[PDB]
Image (tube, coloured by chain):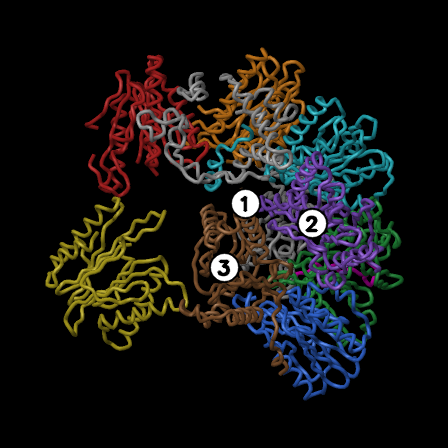
Chain colours: A yellow, B red, C blue, D purple, G green, H brown, I orange, J cyan
Amino acid sequence: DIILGIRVQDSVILASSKAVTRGISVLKDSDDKTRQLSPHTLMSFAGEAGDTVQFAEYIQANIQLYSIREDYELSPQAVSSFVRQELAKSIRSRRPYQVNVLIGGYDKKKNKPELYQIDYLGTKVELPYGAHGYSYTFFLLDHHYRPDMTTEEGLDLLKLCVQELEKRMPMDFKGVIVKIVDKDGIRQVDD
Amino acid sequence: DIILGIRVQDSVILASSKAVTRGISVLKDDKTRQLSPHTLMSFAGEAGDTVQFAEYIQANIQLYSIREDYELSPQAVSSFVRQELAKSIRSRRPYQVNVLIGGYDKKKNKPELYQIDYLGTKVELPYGAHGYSYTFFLLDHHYRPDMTTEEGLDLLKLCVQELEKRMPMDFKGVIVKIVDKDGIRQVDDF
Amino acid sequence: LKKGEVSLGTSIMAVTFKDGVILGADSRTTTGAYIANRVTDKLTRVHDKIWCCRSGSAADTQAIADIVQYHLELYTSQYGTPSTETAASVFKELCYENKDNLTAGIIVAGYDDKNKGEVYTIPLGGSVHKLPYAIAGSGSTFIYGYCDKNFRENMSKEETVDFIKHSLSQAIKWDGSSGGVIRMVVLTAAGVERLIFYPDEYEQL
Amino acid sequence: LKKGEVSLGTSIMAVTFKDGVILGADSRTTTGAYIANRVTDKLTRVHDKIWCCRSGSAADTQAIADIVQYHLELYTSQYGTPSTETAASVFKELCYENKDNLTAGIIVAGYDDKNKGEVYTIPLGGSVHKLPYAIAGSGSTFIYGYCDKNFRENMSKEETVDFIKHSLSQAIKWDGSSGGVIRMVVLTAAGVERLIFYPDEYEQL
Amino acid sequence: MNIVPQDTFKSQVSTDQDKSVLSSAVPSLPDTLRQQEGGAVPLSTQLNDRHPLESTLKNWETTQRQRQMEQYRQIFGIAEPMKRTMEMEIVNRTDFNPLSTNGSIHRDILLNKECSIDWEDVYPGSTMVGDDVHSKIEKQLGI
Amino acid sequence: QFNPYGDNGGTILGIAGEDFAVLAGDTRNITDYSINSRYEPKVFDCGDNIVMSANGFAADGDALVKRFKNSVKWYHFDHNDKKLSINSAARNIQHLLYGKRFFPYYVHTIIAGLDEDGKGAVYSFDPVGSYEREQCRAGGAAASLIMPFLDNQVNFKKPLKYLSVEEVIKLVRDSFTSATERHIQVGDGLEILIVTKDGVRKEFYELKRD
Amino acid sequence: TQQPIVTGTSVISMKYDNGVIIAADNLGSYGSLLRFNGVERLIPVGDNTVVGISGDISDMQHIERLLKDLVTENAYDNPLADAEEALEPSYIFEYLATVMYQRRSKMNPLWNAIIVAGVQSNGDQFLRYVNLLGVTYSSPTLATGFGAHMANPLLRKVVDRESDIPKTTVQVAEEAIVNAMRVLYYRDARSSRNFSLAIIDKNTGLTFKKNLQVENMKWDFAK
Amino acid sequence: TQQPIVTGTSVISMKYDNGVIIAADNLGSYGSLLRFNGVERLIPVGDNTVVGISGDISDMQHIERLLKDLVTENAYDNPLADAEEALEPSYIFEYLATVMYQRRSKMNPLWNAIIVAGVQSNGDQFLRYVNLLGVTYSSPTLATGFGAHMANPLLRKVVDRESDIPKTTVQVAEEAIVNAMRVLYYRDARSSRNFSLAIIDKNTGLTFKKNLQVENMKWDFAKD
Amino acid sequence: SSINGGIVVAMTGKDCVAIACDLRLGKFEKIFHYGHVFLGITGLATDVTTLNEMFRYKTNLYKLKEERAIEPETFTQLVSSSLYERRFGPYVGPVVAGINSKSGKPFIAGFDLIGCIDEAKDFIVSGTASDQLFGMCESLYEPNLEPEDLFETISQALLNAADRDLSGWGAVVYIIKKDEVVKRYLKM
Amino acid sequence: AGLSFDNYQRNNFLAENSHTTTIVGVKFNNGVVIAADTRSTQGPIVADKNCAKLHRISPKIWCAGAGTAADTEAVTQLIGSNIELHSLYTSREPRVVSALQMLKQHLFKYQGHIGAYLIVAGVDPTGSHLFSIHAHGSTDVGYYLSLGSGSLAAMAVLESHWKQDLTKEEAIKLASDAIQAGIWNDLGSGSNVDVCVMEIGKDAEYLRNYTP
């Protein structure tokens, strides 16, 4: 369960690895570790099985309800704050569960991309780039990151990071599903 | 840490890892001891005790060969190794150790391979492996008692390719030695 | 017994004599090897002529005693003076129904015009027993045989006073948590009488 | 003590009187709640007029008693009849030098021409105390006050016999590890006398 | 006046604590080849994880004899333990049979074990090095 | 921590014929190395020609049997005294067992009767509820000493279909006698209930403990 | 609760040809200390039932309160409570077993062993045992605690099986019960010399004997 | 030993201008039971030295045996071992401290606290303390156990500094120590009313008082 | 290479014995002979080999000194003593079978890990499970069987045990008479 | 020498890694009787239905044990060898007191690690003796003793019907009845009864399967 998010000048790129289960062989083409919160806000999650998907679907249902009720789209900041509040409320009276969330959006009012990361305790931090899973790659991002990079440069950096992760992984690392959030909405890259 | 042994109809092929100790990176074989001109021993397991045991065994066997002016049979060598290993842990906590002994009995002109675990259970096997958690699938499906040395080398190369498919860059390679009627040789190309 | 509480390690006695009852105790409260309070009045009163002595946990026993005094005030407002049996029953019910949460043991002495003085004991657990005399506490174990060899039915007041004084003096002598002065309450038809005996008097016995 | 090891939950009383010493005990050996032996001879003879009673581990006390008897035989082969002080010293040395591995406690009652009968007590740990009288065991805790109140110096033989009988009867009554018959050994200048008392005798005291 | 053996542990350890198996090349280190203990037995392993009864058994009879000697010294004097020890030493020193480990008859008579059997007697107790007569001669004569 | 469970031993056996069923059990209730009772039945007639037996913790088995009997009584009250089938009873027992999934009964259950067609039927239940229909089932601490005897002296493929009730009774008696000889817990009696279209018949035999 | 504090030891009961006999000693022990003497551990319910309880004394008194409440409620509002509308031993045992199992399932059990003995209206003897786990069983002879290991063989020597019940007179059963109590007093550290006995007979009714002492003690084989 | 079984309560000592005063109660308690009432915990060693031991009774008796052996051996083969060969408190304390430390290093310590008091040959007061771990220290006032928490504050109000020693007389120090013993008897479950006192002076030489009881006890306010 | 554990069954027929042991197929047998005495050891493989070597040593010395082969009862006592020697470091389940050369009576016995002897007049089962196989042997055993009948019974018991839990399961059976010993293999 | 401690650490390592009766003695006016049951069980399974639990130390000194069977047998055999050697050395009939001393000292030497609880009966020229020996080295003297899992029923029977002056036949009957009660009322006891009777001046009489 490894998730990455890179924010470039005009868009946000989110990459997620194929979900696997212990002792179970599955062949499918789907993204079950990512939910589209809104046409311009995407969410990726990684953590314990069961709880994480329930939390993600709960968040998606709440955000869709708000969008229908108000006939308007929430900003990425408001979405991230709501997710943080709900995550803090979830472990209010129970043992905390492992979960890490990357939220990437394109604020139309500010006309700029944004990316946030929330850990299992409910700590929301705005980041230029972020990753979770294997604990290697932060040095590669640091040496090859610029705030004014284009989409193609971000995709090249993501390809380099994916190759580096695959090399260390014992060849069990399958493909990576890549999505781009920008002014035109959310799309998936099949390259 | 994986040690492999294949007994082909007229030879014994022993394969071992190159070198790894703690998190220290070294360039640099320290896992195979030549017990006799026609008998080789490959040891794997805990670092510090296995080397001492192997050196003790090699010293004893060399002393016997010097005294008798004769080469001890691989079966007797295996029995002595098993007895010494059982004696070493008779008054202390056992330590992880696995030994593969490959020899060529000149009196019978037959290759032989033996495996001894940490408690001292000697088993005569056509093929053996330790350190892999499997690899017995290839060693069982594509093994014949009448395989030539080239076929055994090809099977070992397939096993090494399988190993170099789910391991990091730390896997330096495999050191291969062959014991036969002409003695002990080291394989560089394969 | 919850950790860090206060234990009522003491020497409690109650003896029934011809004209009523006498309840006696020591005055030492210790926390480990340190005497926290060397002057303690352990003769708790729950009604005008119904008294009790407590053991176990101080907080639980005090709460139970307060509730019992409340209950007896309600009873007196309704029906009048209760008998010692009713007070013992209330004590037993309170101790038994909460025995999984509270550790408490009570010795109840009482007097009334019908029964003419009675002694009841509720040990840990909640059972009730009616006896001609009762002893309790950590220091009681050293006087058992003595109390079995010097008790007579229908003793006079002075004989009972001397018996209680001697037994409590021995218990104080042989127990580390028993000491100080001896306090005795005499419940008869005449009324309630208080007696205090100092170490220099009972240590010469 | 060790797991599964027999423990000596006895009642031991040694009393010095005008003409010598008397050592008495009960006869019960228990296994927690089941009585393994209803009749036991807990009075161990170390020398002709030097007897003892044991508490703690049974095996350790038996080994110590055997070694002390052997030592006293060796001493007698050289210098004649030993003294109670010598036997107590040997017991104390054996118990103290081995207290890290053996659990043992002894009560020694002796007689000799010089000292005219003496009592020594060696509790757990290996310290020797010379006392006019000594009590030990599980039941001894119930007769501390009684023995303290009813002990006199230079009593007659019958008075000491009655005192020990009453005290041991109370100890048997209040303790679950004390048995039926009472065995007493009287060591005087005339010789060694053995007395036995049955429950139907002392239960009616 | 001990009954159970005491002070059976070692206060200090060293690499040359056994002078009989010292290496000739480096006299400050043990010789593992002549030890014939398997070659993987460091001395440290002999300090931990031992049965709590082995020390009691291996030092039982010695402790009993020492207690007996102490009693003799206390009661009889110094001459009796001195004579007992002298006789035992004379018997032990004059017996040298490299081909057997069984004790002599006179030793058993002195120890009062003429008609006594223990598990030591029933179970008294290949190698390329150090199992010949010459090694025992060197050990006996301090060569 | 209070331990709510226990064990009382005992052995039960259920066999299905072609037109009958047999359920037998040893009538000895024992605690650890002590005999509580030399005659305590563990097989009961639970209504409409259905025999039930829960082996293991005695209190749990008694509670389960009591609950099932009350459920059968209310079933008769609700539906015009309709006869309860063996499969419906099996599902009822499954629900009763699974209703205590997190505080399970410490019993193994066997029931026997006749199916709709009229053949013998035996159902076996694990403590949490899972059940299946079997030709023969042995439960308790003697099954390893009873099943091989039956497999040796009869075939379930002399075929079991051709056996009569007397032969089945004889085989059960012989197997239980052998188990009594070999096993300490088994003995002191054997009660057998036979279910046919005529009803339920009870027989008793004395084993080697009196 | 978690453990008994003041405890009783043993109750022993037997069936004979005309009724049942039960017995139990009068003692409440505080650990190894024999603290309370004069504790009645046999409860006569009705004119034909006797309940013997061994174990925690407080729980025994609670069960006594429950039995008294049951007896009082039986007369509400039956005018024939002394008549054929009395309480059978089977009713009392069923109620007690239900209570014990319900409390066991609630993780707050009553640390007791209960033996219910009596004679039914038709004259059939009733004798059942229940414990803190709710385990119930019947037998011609029953006992609790150390009685279950020592007195039980002595009683079974008399009434070995069901066929021996009609052959056992009341005198034989009473003598066997007295001998078993004597053995228990011999070999039980927590036992007492004083005990109570109850005989329930379909002809003579209920006979309750108190202040019975163990006699014929053999201690002379010492010296 | 692994753990003590029969134990003592406390020993308190202080210095006055002409010597030292030490005191300790007489009681041996078996757990929570006050078993023995004749135990003496003050041992006069030599001519003008007193040793007070608190703790395990068996180890205290062992230490008493050691002190007796030391006294006998010092005078052994020395007919003039009475004026110049008399044992000084410093030597006895050094021996005891060395024994305690060596046994601590053996993992078999003596469960005791030892206070050595006396007057040196040149008239100087000596007062030192050692524990089971072998740690030793000196001070104008010393105490053990509960006396280290209650008796020490009372004694330091009389002798707080080294310059206060010449200002303190024998009567003042004795009264302070008696008051401290009375306070300890007030607020100690394991304490005993009886106690023993020892005054070591450079003029009189020694004064050992036994069978002293706590007097002037105030319990009248308990009437209210 | 796991070879720890196994099953050994010993039975007595009219004037013969039968000792059978499980195999693993996919060279390591658990039955050894020292003349006319057979020993089967189950448990740790290293302990089995050690006991085999030690008993070969002791039997060779016994034959050299006594000038005769050791009897099954004497060998049973020797095995018991050897097992009790390692009281605090005990090794396994040994089974001894044979026929006395003089009396001719069959003899079978079993041992625990510290040499407690259980002499059975009917049969001995040694192994880890020892529950299904024990029941099958109990059901199939009949006293006083002929060597052919005894062989059939023991082979059927082993086959039934094998059926109720493989690809590489085998068995070795010895039918021992006073003058002839027959060794057979079962391949299931 | 002696019992070995080898492979103790190996056994502990394997263990950490998941690699794993009624006897009575009755003393009568001219001798002693010792009786025992004859069932050997390996847990629930009855291994043998007729086993001899009466072992002999000396021709007139017998014993029966419980606990660890191997330890009991080994200790009994060793004490028998020592007793025979002592009798040969002294040319005298062995005494039960000597066997008691040897057993006590041997059991105390191992500090309870040798689990063997014994009832030892015998007759020597000084009289008849009956002792109970615990595994830690403590011995007790009594007139009637019981041992094993069925010892409670046996003790009840013995307490019911014991007198000071008993004949040989009465003692045999009492021992048989105690063993029978243990057999019937205890699951670990069963089968037949073995008896051994020892009088003064007469040979020991050993009756196997006295009551079948």
Q: Residues within 10 Å of mark 1 (few under 14, many from 20)?
A: few
Q: In the drawing, does residue J47 fall left or right of residue G83?
A: left
Front residue (pair F146, G6):
G6
Are tags 3 and 2 found on a single chain?
Answer: no
Q: Which image quarter: residue G3?
A: bottom right
Q: Position of residue F129 (x, y in %)?
A: 54, 54
Q: Name which residue lies at 32% across and 69% down.
A: A61
Disc 2 and disc 1 in contact, CB within 8 angstroms: no
First reached walking from the N terminus: tag 3 or tag 1: 1
Q: In the drawing, does residue I110 fall left or right of residue F189?
A: left
Indicate whether J40 appears above or below E86: below
Q: Position of residue C2 (x, y in %)?
A: 54, 66
Q: Chain of mark 2?
A: D
Secondary element type, mark 2: strand
Residue named by callout 2? D107
Q: Position of residue I74 (x, y in %)?
A: 62, 20
Of all residues shown, which one is farthest toward the bottom? C77
Q: Which image quarter: residue E59?
A: top right
The answer to whether residue H98 is visible is: yes
Q: Chain of mark 1?
A: H
Residue named by callout 3? H117
Residue named by callout 1? H79
Instruction: Judge whether residue G113 is colored magenta.
Output: yes
How many numbered circles are shown?
3
Residue span colored magenta: G111-126
Q: Chain of mark 3?
A: H
Instruction: Judge whether residue D158 is colored magenta.
Output: no
Indicate whether C177 appears above or below B118: below
